[PDB]
Length: 10
Ligand SMILES: *C(=O)CCCCCCCCCCCCC
Image (cartoon, rainbow, N blue to C red; front, side, top):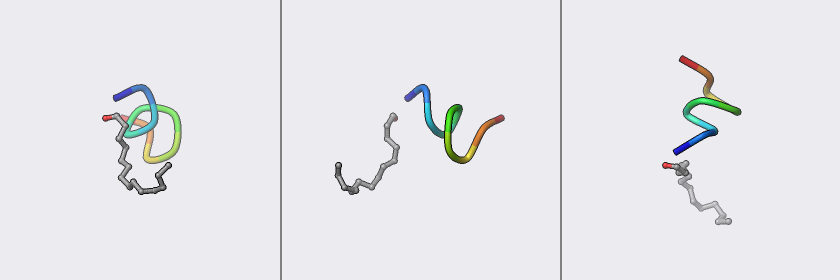
């Protein structure tokens, strides 16, 4: 959830 945000970001 933070990845998409942290990995993926945005
Ligand atoms: C927040 O929603 C985290 C989800 C980010 C997507 C990860 C999907 C892939 C999961 C398998 C990778 C190995 C598991 C740690």
